[PDB]
Length: 217
Ligand SMILES: CN1CCC(C#N)(NC(=O)[C@H](CC2CCCCC2)NC(=O)N2CCOCC2)CC1
Picture 1: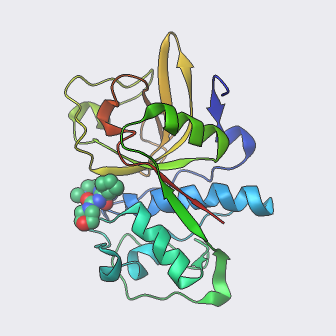
Picture 2: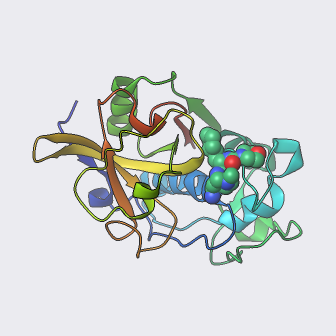
């Protein structure tokens, strides 16, 4: 496997989004993963509608809109729905709204999704290198997470009790510290222009490899 990977260099990652006061991290994680696959398949980079997931992938998928959701069930909704609209056609409002999906605005489809084995960072590395960005959950509740600015994030108080859905778009090594390149959805003001490098191969730090999954088209 390559020593390092960064899907941004392959034009497979869209601009960092700002979820605001709506707990839609799961939706942004899911669309980010599908966006890479869409780019890989069609050659076109297109932001997908996180709002579409918030408003439509709901109760039936065990999701709660602005109150939380799952990337895997969001993927299944896209499969069941036979599509997901573009962000431009169905903009993000950081609120729970009535489902307004319209296939006339469909920008991607999903045929299946895969959940990686729990806590295996080597398997996660293989997937990020060979398949594309991977949706994951991390423990982002520690004060240090919000204040991250640079370097490689390592928090002794971190746990494998994850609460925040984000996207791994790469991995590598910085000054002797291996890391996972993570795309957050708290806008460009957070961390390194919206990204955070989180410790890799450090005992599944913050649960980053606890619940990984990626869709396919
Ligand atoms: C509790 N609050 C809700 C929104 C948030 C995001 N944004 N997190 C979530 O949506 C997380 C993401 C999930 C990804 C997969 C591994 C486990 C975590 N989910 C989540 O909080 N719920 C609670 C409601 O029932 C559905 C799941 C931040 C924390």
